[PDB]
Amino acid sequence: FTLDADF
Image (cartoon, rainbow, N blue to C red; front, side, top):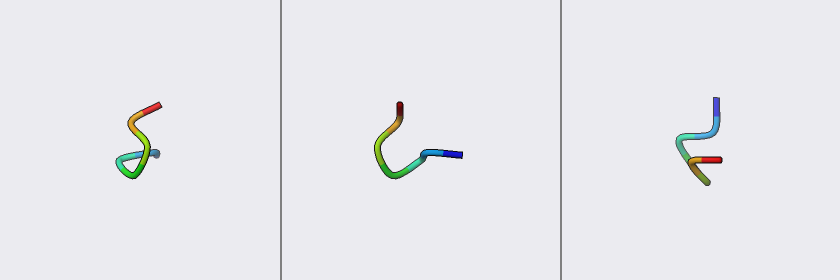
């Protein structure tokens, strides 16, 4: 999902 932002 967002393993860029986390959230």
